[PDB]
Image: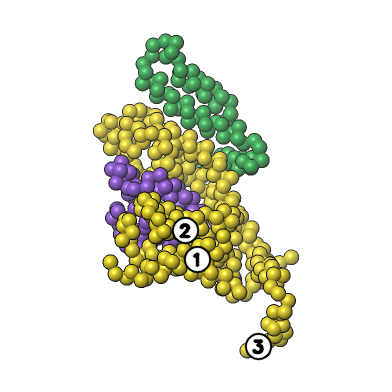
Amino acid sequence: ISNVLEWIIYTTGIIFVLPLFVEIPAHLQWQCGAIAVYFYWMNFLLYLQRFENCGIFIVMLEVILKTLLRSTVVFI
Amino acid sequence: AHMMNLGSYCLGLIPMTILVVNIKPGMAFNTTNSYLIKTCMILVFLSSIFGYISNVLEWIIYTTGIIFVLPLFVEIPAHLQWQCGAIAVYFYWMNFLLYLQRFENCGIFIVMLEVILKTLLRSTVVFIFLLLAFGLSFYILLNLQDPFSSPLLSIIQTFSMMLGDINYRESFLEPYLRNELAHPVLSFAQLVSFTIFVPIVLMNLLIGLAVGDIADVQKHASLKRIAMQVELHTSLEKKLPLWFLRKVDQKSTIVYQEIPNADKS
Amino acid sequence: FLLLAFGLSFYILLNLQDPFSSPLLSIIQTFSMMLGDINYRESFLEPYLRNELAHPVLSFAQLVSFTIFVPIVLMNLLIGL
């Protein structure tokens, strides 16, 4: 749900910008930057869940995706 | 009357086809058949000014038509003119669909398409943040490789990726065996996540909206159509002068796949 | 009439490139393009890096519009019927 997203996003943001305050490998930092961006935005969708125009769209998408995961265990 | 309006638009439509089918793409503006072209050209220039959602379409189409044929009355760059010709053609025809919105055979089809497309645009703002996010993630993981250089290429590429083909599974594999692509461990994960979130689920949901609303329109389709014809005749009746009434009117008629039973209250 | 319109637009933007020479090839090509594969995203990209293809600015727009109006929405509506 939303709170492990709130966890992961911040920690990856931190790795993303530490090397101003230490020396660290450079590629690694750049690497986990990718994850930071991606999770960042997709998380941001759930904030856009609220309002009127979107507000119906996303609940639809979350529910359909949970419906997807039972299927994903059996075709996994 | 109706056809007459179409025709005013029609003697515009067949021109475009003739000019761009007959000659040619490239030439600054080219050699016989010279009359076919002169006639159609002047006819178009005149077909443009007559009148001057649907009205910004009525704006854009005419102005682009004008750029399309000015260089007979000035010197201008040639490629530019040819370029905005493309837009002119495309918008031209798609606009023409809305005139075909009227009548019976089509008359239901298109309202369906416009409504479904508006239903599409809320979705397009929210995956214009989502697909954008994916766009950038793929931007970062493989822009050693070409094409992924620069943001814009990446996002447009992923956009194309939505459709169907992945596609360009000749773009992970070969790097990976090359060992060119950095971050195998993560990147494969990225693609499996990607297919869990756009090729399959998003598409299916969009399909879901499609089916829901189209089903809803067809549920009481007949009224939408007949309300189209009555509306048109009432808003034709009011403008035309009273003395041109009965005639035409028989107020009688000699007599010498229609509408579905299943819908009911 | 609609797919014909698209056919001609792609006719004008990339008929330096082959196949788009002549109307008939173009319209049939776009027709095939409806199905699914774009497909032939090996037909914009490489020109563009070549810098062969004229009108990048507009043309990319043309393809994004195109995918908004046939691969996704039209197909889904036909599915709807």
Q: Residue at x 31, y 34 (%)?
A: B145
Picture mark count: 3
Residue that label 1 marks: B47
Q: What subunit carries mark 2?
A: B
Say few, some or many: other residues with alpha carbon within 10 Å of mark 3 (under 14 / 14 to 19 / 20 or more).
few
Q: What subunit carries mark 3?
A: B
Res. A62 visible in picture: yes
For badge 2, the amino acid type reads Gly
Image position, residue B163 (x, y; %): 44, 48
- Chain C color in figure: purple
Q: Residue at x 59, y 33 (%)?
A: A46
Which tag, 3 or 1, sits closer to the chain's start?
1
With respect to residue B235, does A28 lie above or below? above
- Chain A color in figure: green
Res. C7 visible in picture: no
Residue that label 2 marks: B65
Indicate which disc residue B255 carries: 3
Indicate which disc residue B160 carries: none
Could you say which is closer to the camera, residue B202 or residue A47? A47
